[PDB]
Amino acid sequence: AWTQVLLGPGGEPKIKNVVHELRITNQV
Amino acid sequence: AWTQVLLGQAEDKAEVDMDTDAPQVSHKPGGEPKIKNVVHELRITNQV
């Protein structure tokens, strides 16, 4: 259930959003 | 830091931090010098 809910009786898996910011600090 | 401000560095050649993951606000070891733009004047008095 975690495997199928991860790709978009087994319970309810809560697979949370991971927040990422692409980032410039000093031209990098 | 005084040596860096005397050379006239503008420092938008390291372009500005959008968020606050070290946006260069610090009580620095260099500090923040602002050197005066002192004007020396060329003129003429008595044909000199």
Image: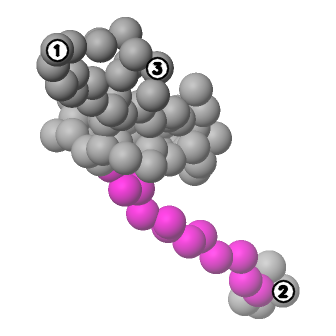
Identity of the residue drawn at 73% across and 83% down: B43
> Crowding at label 3, few (<14), some or many (≥20) Cα neighbours within 10 Å?
few
Towards the viewer: B33 or B13: B13
Residue type beneath disc 2: Gln
Query: x, y percentage for residue A22?
Result: 51, 33
Question: Mark 2 vs mark 3: same chain?
Answer: no
Residue A9's disc number: 1
Residue type beneath disc 3: Leu
Query: x, y percentage for residue B14?
Result: 57, 37
Towards the viewer: B10 or B41: B10
Residue located beneath label 3 in the image:
A7
Q: CA–CA distance between discs 1 and 3?
A: 19 Å
Towards the viewer: B44 or B12: B12
Q: Give left or right: position of A23 versus B27.
A: right
Q: Give left or right: position of B13 versus A22.
A: right
Tell me where residue A8 sits by quadrant.
top left
Residue located beneath label 2 in the image:
B47
Q: Which residues are magenta?
A: B33-44
Report the chain holding disc 1: A
Query: x, y percentage for residue B10?
Result: 57, 50
Asked whether the viewer can see residue B33, the reply is yes
Identity of the residue drawn at 37% across and 47% down: B19
Q: Is residue A1 magenta?
A: no
Report the chain holding disc 3: A
Q: Give left or right: position of B11 versus B26.
A: right
> Crowding at label 2, few (<14), some or many (≥20) Cα neighbours within 10 Å?
few
**Circle nearer the viewer, 1 or 2:** 1
Tell me where residue A6 sits by quadrant.
top left
Location of residue A14 with respect to B31 vertically, above or below: above
> Crowding at label 1, few (<14), some or many (≥20) Cα neighbours within 10 Å?
few
Identity of the residue drawn at 71% across and 76% down: B42
Q: What secondary structure is found at the residue carrying circle 1?
A: loop
